[PDB]
C-alpha cells in the first residue's frame, strides 16, 4: 500500500494504542453479529446464537487476537502485503472457500471498532489511511 | 428486511443521534470524500474541503432524509420516492458508493456514540442503511 | 423495490415458464454446481452429478418456491418467511451464492425462452431475484 | 485462466459462431438496461431512456463491438490476461473510475447474451468455461 509519511505515522501512532486482546474479538464478534452468514465458517466455536453469546465467546476472542496478529504483521509489511498473505490467502481461498467480499466486510468492521475505541482520536484522515490499509489487506487475501 | 427488534434499535439509536444529526452527516460526508475519493465525482459543483459550508448543509440534508426514513421505516419506498427519483433517475449513483457512505455513517456513529454502538445496534443500523441504499438505487 | 411494470414483466415471464419450472430450476442448479463449485459445499448430502434425481427434485422445490414468490410479489417477506428461516438461520448461506444462482436462473431463462428475454424482462427478473435474495438472506 | 483442452475447444468452437456486430451492442445494451447506473458512464451516447432507445442506439452497437474486440483479444491470450488488459485497466480505473464489480456485471450479462444466442447449444459446461473466462477478464481489468 502506497501511503504518505503522515498516514504511516498516523496508522503507527494509533495502532500502538490498540488493545489487541480486545479489538480482535471485538472486530471478529461484530463480524459474526452484523454479517451472520460468516457464522457458518465458525460453527466449531460453540454457541453463536445471540450477540451477547458471540461477544462473550472465548474462541472468538482468541481467534480475533489471531486476526489482529495478521493485521499487525500486515502493518509491518505495507509494501509486501501479497508476500505476507500468501499462506493465509491459500487457507482462506482453498481450504475454507471464504468469498473475497467477506474480507472487505471484516476490514470495514475493524475500522468501525477502531472508531468505537478512539472516538475523536479517529479523525477522517486516520480513517482514510486505515481504509486504504484495510483494502490492501483484503485485496492481498483475495488473491 | 428488518425485524421488529432492529426497527426498535434503529429508532432508538437514531433518536439518540437527534440534534447532532447535521454534524454527523457532514462528518460522514467528509469521511466518504476523504477515504473514498471517487465519490467526489458526484459533486463537481461543491467545495469539498474540510469544514466547508456546502458539505455541512448537504450533510444536514442527508441526515434529515435518514431521520424521516427512520420515521417511515415500515414503508420506506413511498417515503423516499422523491430521493429515489433523484439518486436513481437523475444522478445514476453506483450502489457501491451507497455502501461506502453507509460505512462512513457507521464510523461516525462509532466515533460519537460508543455507549450506543452495541453490536446489535450495529447490525440494525447496517441493514437499515442497506435498506435505504436498496430503496434509493432502485428505480420504480 | 419493484415498479408496477417489472411486476408485470416477472408475472408474465414466469407465467410463460409454467410447467417447465422444475426442469429450469434443475438446470439452473446444475449450472450453478458446475460453473460455481463452491456452492457444492452447501449440499454435502446430495448426489451432484448431471441428471441426478435429487438435484431434479430440489430444482422442482426451488422453482415452486419462485412461483410462490411471483404469486405473492408484493408481500415477499410474509410469504417467504419459512424459507428465510431456512436459508438465513439454519443454513446461513452467503448472499454471494444467491447472486450466483440468480445468474444461473437468468442463463436458463436465456437458453430456453429467447422470445421472452426482452432486455426489460431481463432487468425485471434480475430485480425480482435480487429481491428474493434480499428476503432469504435476512432474519426476521 | 486455467482451462482444460475441452473447455478451450468449447469456448473456441462456440465463439467462432458469435456475431460480433450483435452480441457486442446487445451485451452492452443489456448492461445499460439491467444495471442503469452504468448509463452514467455513457452519457455521451445520446438517448438512453427506454430499453428500445438503448438497443436502438448506434454508439452502443459500435462500442459493444469494441468490447467484444477486447473479449476476443482476451480469448487469444488466456494465459496473459493481465498483460492484455493493462491499458484497459489503466483506462477503466484511472480515467473512468469504473468500480471493479461493474466488470463482473458486464461479464455475466455477456454470458446471458451467449445463452440467448445459442440456447441448448450453450450447455452448462460451456457456461462453466465462459464463467472462468469472464471472471478472468473481470479480474484482469480490476487490477
Ligand atoms: C480480512 C482479514 C482476515 C484476516 C487478517 C484473517 C486472519 C486469519 C488468520 C491469521 C488465520 C489463521 C488461524 C490459525 O491458523 O490458527 C485465520 C483463519 C481462519 N479464518 Fe480468517 N482472516 C480474515 C478474514 C476472514 C473472514 C472474513 C473469514 C470468514 C467469514 C475468515 C475465516 C477464517 C476461518 C474459518 C479460519 C480457520 C479458523 C478455524 O477453523 O477455527 N477469515 N484467519
Ligand atoms: C445513503 C443515504 C443517502 C441519503 C439519505 C441521501 C440523501 C440526499 C439528499 C437529502 C439530497 C438533497 C436533495 C436535494 O437537495 O434536492 C441528496 C442529493 C445528492 N446526493 Fe445523496 N443521499 C444518500 C447517498 C448518496 C451517495 C452515496 C451519493 C454519491 C456518492 C449521493 C450523491 C448525491 C448527490 C450528487 C446529490 C446532489 C447534490 C446537489 O444537488 O447539490 N447521495 N441526497
Ligand atoms: C432464489 C433463490 C432460492 C430459492 C427460492 C430456494 C428455495 C429453496 C427451497 C424450496 C428449498 C427446500 C426447502 C425444504 O425442502 O425444506 C431450499 C433448500 C435449500 N437451499 Fe435453497 N433456494 C434458493 C437459493 C439457494 C442458494 C443460492 C443456496 C446455496 C448456494 C441454497 C441452498 C439450499 C440448501 C443447502 C437447502 C437444503 C436442501 C436440503 O437440505 O436437502 N439455496 N431452498
Ligand atoms: C469485462 C468488461 C469490459 C471490457 C472488456 C471493456 C472494454 C473496453 C474497451 C475495448 C474500450 C475502448 C477503449 C478505447 O476505445 O480507447 C472501453 C472503454 C470504455 N469502457 Fe469498457 N470494458 C469493460 C467494462 C466496462 C464497464 C462495466 C463499464 C461501465 C459501467 C465500462 C465503461 C467504459 C467507458 C466509459 C469507456 C470509454 C468509452 C467512451 O467514453 O465513449 N467498461 N472498454
Image (spheres, coloured by chain):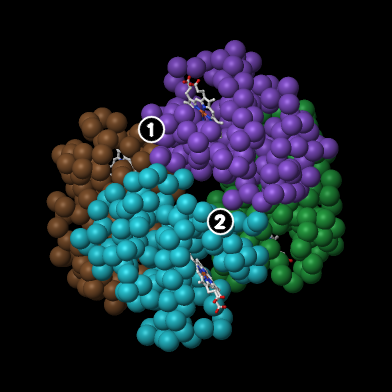
Chain colours: A green, B purple, C cyan, D brown
* Residue at mark 2 to residue at mark 1: CA–CA distance: 27 Å
Q: Mark 1 falls on what kind of element?
A: helix
Chain of the residue on which disc 1 is drawn: B
The residue lying at 26 percent from left, 36 percent from top is D48
Q: Which of A129 and C97 is in front in this view?
A: C97
Q: Is residue C49 left or right of residue A96?
A: left
Q: Mark 2 falls on what kind of element?
A: helix
Q: Is residue D54 above or below residue A100?
A: above
Q: Is residue B120 above or below residue D49?
A: below
x, y percentage for residue B114? 80, 37
Q: Is residue A118 left or right of residue B93?
A: right
Residue underneath mark 1: B89
> Which disc is residue C31 wearing?
none
Q: Is residue A99 visible?
A: no
The residue lying at 54 percent from left, 62 percent from top is C80
The residue lying at 43 percent from left, 87 percent from top is C53
Q: Which residue lies furthest to the top in this view?
A: B53
**To which quarter of the image does residue A28 belong?**
bottom right
Chain of the residue on which disc 2 is drawn: C
Bin the neighbour count of mark 1 within 10 Å (Cα to Cα): few under 14, some 14-19, many 20 and up: some
**To which quarter of the image does residue C20 belong?**
bottom left
> Which disc is residue C77 wearing?
2
x, y percentage for residue D92? 37, 40
Q: Can residue D46 be seen in this view?
A: yes
The answer to whether mark 2 is within 8 Å of ligand 3 is no
- Total marks in image: 2
Amino acid at each position: 500500500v502506497h501511503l504518505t509519511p503522515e498516514e504511516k505515522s498516523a496508522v503507527t501512532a494509533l495502532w500502538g494504542k490498540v488493545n489487541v486482546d480486545e479489538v480482535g474479538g471485538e472486530a471478529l464478534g461484530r463480524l459474526l453479529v452484523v454479517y451472520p452468514w460468516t457464522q457458518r465458517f465458525f460453527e466449531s466455536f460453540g454457541d453463536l446464537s445471540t450477540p451477547d453469546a458471540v461477544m462473550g465467546n472465548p474462541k472468538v476472542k482468541a481467534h480475533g487476537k489471531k486476526v489482529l496478529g495478521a493485521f499487525s504483521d500486515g502493518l509491518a509489511h505495507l509494501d509486501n502485503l501479497k508476500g505476507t498473505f500468501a499462506t493465509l490467502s491459500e487457507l482462506h481461498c482453498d481450504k475454507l472457500h471464504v468469498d473475497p467480499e467477506n474480507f472487505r466486510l471484516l476490514g470495514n468492521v475493524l475500522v468501525c471498532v477502531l472508531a468505537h475505541h478512539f472516538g475523536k482520536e479517529f479523525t477522517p484522515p486516520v480513517q482514510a489511511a486505515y481504509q486504504k490499509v484495510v483494502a490492501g489487506v483484503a485485496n492481498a487475501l483475495a488473491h | 428486511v428488518l425485524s421488529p427488534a432492529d426497527k426498535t434499535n434503529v429508532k432508538a439509536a437514531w433518536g439518540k443521534v437527534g440534534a447532532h444529526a447535521g454534524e454527523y452527516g457532514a462528518e460522514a460526508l467528509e469521511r466518504m470524500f476523504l477515504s473514498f475519493p471517487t465519490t467526489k465525482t458526484y459533486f463537481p459543483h461543491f467545495d469539498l474541503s474540510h469544514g466547508s459550508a456546502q458539505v455541512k448543509g448537504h450533510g444536514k440534508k442527508v441526515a434529515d432524509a435518514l431521520t424521516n426514513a427512520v420515521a417511515h421505516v415500515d414503508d420506506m419506498p413511498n417515503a423516499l420516492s422523491a430521493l429515489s427519483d433523484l439518486h436513481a433517475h437523475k444522478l445514476r449513483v453506483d450502489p457501491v458508493n451507497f455502501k461506502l457512505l453507509s460505512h462512513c455513517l457507521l464510523v461516525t456513529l462509532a466515533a460519537h456514540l460508543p455507549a450506543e454502538f452495541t453490536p446489535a445496534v450495529h447490525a440494525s443500523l447496517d441493514k437499515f442503511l442497506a435498506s435505504v441504499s436498496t430503496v434509493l438505487t432502485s428505480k420504480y
